[PDB]
Amino acid sequence: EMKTVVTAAHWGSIGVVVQDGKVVKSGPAIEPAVPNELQTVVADQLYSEARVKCPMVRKGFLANPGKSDTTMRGRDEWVRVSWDEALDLVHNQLKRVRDEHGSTGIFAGSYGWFSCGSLHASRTLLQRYMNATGGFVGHKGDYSTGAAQVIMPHVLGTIEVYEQQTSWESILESSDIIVLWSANPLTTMRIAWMSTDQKGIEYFKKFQASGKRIICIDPQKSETCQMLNAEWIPVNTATDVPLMLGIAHTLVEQGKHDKDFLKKYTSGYAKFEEYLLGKTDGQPKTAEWAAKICGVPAETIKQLAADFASKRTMLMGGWGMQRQRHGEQTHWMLVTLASMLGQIGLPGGGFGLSYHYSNGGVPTATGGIIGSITASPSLDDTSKSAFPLARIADVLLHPGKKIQYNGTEITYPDIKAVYWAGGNPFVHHQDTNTLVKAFQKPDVVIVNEVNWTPTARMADIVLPATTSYERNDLTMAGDYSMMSVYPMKQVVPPQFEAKNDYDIFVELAKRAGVEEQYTEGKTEMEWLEEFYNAAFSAARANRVAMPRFDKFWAENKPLSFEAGEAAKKWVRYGEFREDPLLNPLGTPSGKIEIFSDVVEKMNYNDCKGHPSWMEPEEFAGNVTEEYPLALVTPHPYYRLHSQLAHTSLRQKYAVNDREPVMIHPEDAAARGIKDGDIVRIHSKRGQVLAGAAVTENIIKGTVALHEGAWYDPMYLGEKPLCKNGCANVLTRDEGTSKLAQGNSPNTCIVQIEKFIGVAPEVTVFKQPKQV
Ligand SMILES: Nc1nc2c(c(=O)[nH]1)N[C@H]1C(S)=C(S)[C@@H](COP(=O)(O)OP(=O)(O)OC[C@H]3O[C@@H](n4cnc5c(=O)[nH]c(N)nc54)[C@H](O)[C@@H]3O)O[C@H]1N2
Ligand SMILES: Nc1nc2c(c(=O)[nH]1)N[C@H]1C(S)=C(S)[C@@H](COP(=O)(O)OP(=O)(O)OC[C@H]3O[C@@H](n4cnc5c(=O)[nH]c(N)nc54)[C@H](O)[C@@H]3O)O[C@H]1N2
Ligand SMILES: [Mo]
Ligand SMILES: [O]
């Protein structure tokens, strides 16, 4: 009559209370250091009226499958169909593309975060089906570190951003200063790719409790800065390279840089110093020069230099500052600065590029790691067609176009079919109006979705998918500690006519005659036992005993491992520092590449051989009369991107039923805007409505609109107005540079005005037309 079921999500292990077959409460299965409200809305996710309840097809698509008026996408009426008919239609439409163009005509990169779980990984299951039927065009990189993950291999010989960090125990014991540079961990570590072990936030609180210095360098006084009682250094968005250069110049000018470290562990510093001192362009990159650009007073720049060089300092760089034009320069320069400080490889010293993401630094436990489903079941030349994924709109609009990327050339393919399963590009991709046009080009657009997202509303065929709570699965506490195996026990039966993505793709696999290769003859629970036994065997090899799967599953509790002393004491780059000749980096020199011949020899206009300041098209430094404010689009506290936007958590932040925009009181007063007013934000790309949140917690001249609000266009006969405040309606869709071609949202300027009139009803969380 009343039971508690343990399952999990990106936002942690979750206990779910079921009362007479209905979910009535959800919360942490393991008490966290800071409450995580994301864990409390399982019932909202299960029973929401925004859920896709039945297979649906666009009316105009039904009239002429694969030959419709595609300008009707997003505008049409929806027809309920049976699963039989929808699956026959999907199979037929994909087969037509394969028959006429082959695998290069299908895009199934399907970027998204979907839900955690080893088996029910909607994106992987889609790609497993696509590969079982001949292949598909995928993508390269990701939206999180599109720039940093390309430049760091050139500088450090490794991807760096998704690797274990120096142990938090070492930071607690030895760091005098931690600098949160474009990092908001008390927001961004409420989730992990698997399931957050919740220990990263705890360690930040332990460091706060030590009383040692925490510095936040950010255009906003973030949730982290406020909750950790930290020192706020306001900085203009996209001006961190000038600030780092000013700090670097001060170090040289005062003889505080570590010349011994630079000599032994880096390559090309001299070429960089010539630029730093103004010997190549005639402009020394002084603190006074930097202050004009980044808004940090020159004397504050100098004191940071002195404090960093005299105290054991860990530079924790987040990723907002590389999600922008020339983003490659920021973490390149951060590494360069850390090299000049000379503390890389010391306890509590150096830099880290994942202390803000998925609990980096939490000591790695000794245990086992479960398996998971792959896209490889057991003529396809799509590898050459993969492109940097943020070029998606460019690809759909310009088939055959060639671009430069990381020293090579890529030719866009000719995409006829788009299948998304577990992502929301009409919220996550930049310049939404251009994406609308791009999605008119494919012959067929298919979406598996839990809810009626803006992406589903732009499709031809929408298939209802289940949540994690309607199926069984396994995940880990992570993403680096690997300290627990979390069970994901089914809480309720599938709702409405929703199906697990697994079952959707089994049915399509049957229609193509590849069911056996897809399922491998296994049931849901047989898949999970196999994944579990992979961890069982690895734990055994590590001298750790685990219960049998059936015992583990019956207990329905997290199974946790312990970290040993080696993990608790581990220092990143410690071996390199001990002996760089015997422990070289995977770079051409074997050292830190402050100057990279490889990058220089590419001869790109927007990326030189060493870190440099290159003014972007739009930022605080070149706002105009027409667009006098700069924009930054940080990640939200009460959503995972667009996930949970439809839940009761919306009431915790919506202002006048719009996404809130942080605006400085001086910029608000100049516009007659008071707290709580609906405002109109517009750029050269589009216009959205938001709710004014007037606050000194944002640097003057800049406004912050969090990413992830559901695009809700108001069609009034054109770049229609978003009624809800989707940030990417406003952003530029362009590569960071020819090196990485990452996405560049956070270099943007806008205008804001008080909205006069009656506020449009927000309709994007309700069933669409003709359900
Ligand atoms: N202006 C700006 N834009 C940005 C960013 C920014 O910082 N500023 N950040 C970028 C980055 S780092 C990210 S990773 C992206 C996020 O981009 P997305 O990953 O697309 O955002 P999500 O809201 O997580 O979308 C996940 C979708 O998967 C669905 N889903 C969940 N579980 C399942 C399932 O089991 N089956 C199926 N079929 N669907 C499921 C959810 O309903 C949800 O719609 O945004 C990027 N865009
Ligand atoms: N609750 C929640 N947690 C999450 C996510 C979520 O959507 N919701 N997204 C997850 C995923 S997919 C990702 S990739 C990571 C994102 O990890 P991050 O990229 O670090 O998340 P952002 O909010 O974009 O972090 C940028 C922070 O630095 C600021 N900032 C932005 N641009 C600049 C700049 O140019 N210079 C300086 N000095 N500061 C800048 C932002 O205001 C913001 O406070 O977080 C993950 N964790
Ligand atoms: Mo991300
Ligand atoms: O990501």
Image (cartoon, helix red, strand yellow):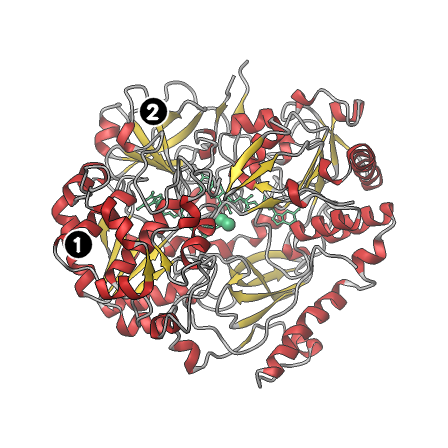
Is the residue marked 2 within 8 Å of ligand 1, measured from its CB? Answer: no
**Of 427 and 285, which appears nearest the observer?**
285
Tell me residue 444's x, y (percent): 72, 31
Q: Residue 497 in the image: state x and y as whole percent.
A: 75, 45
Contact check, label 1 and label 2, Cβ < 8 Å: no
**The residue under label 2 is which amino acid type?**
Gln
The residue shown at (43%, 33%) is 658
Would you place residue 178 above or below residue 611 in this image?
below
| 659 to 122, vertically: above or below | above
Examine the image and state in which quarter residue 98 appears. Answer: top right
Is residue 141 shown left or right of residue 312? Answer: right
Foreground pick, 320 / 230: 320
Residue 421 place in picture, x, y as percent: 66, 44
Foreground residue among 176 and 192:
176
Could one spot residue 157 in this view of the protein?
Answer: yes
Residues under labels 1 and 2: Cα distance? Answer: 40 Å
Which residue bears the numbered disc 2?
751
Crowd around label 2: few <14 · some 14–19 · many ≥20 (10 Å): many
- Residue ID for mark 1: 252
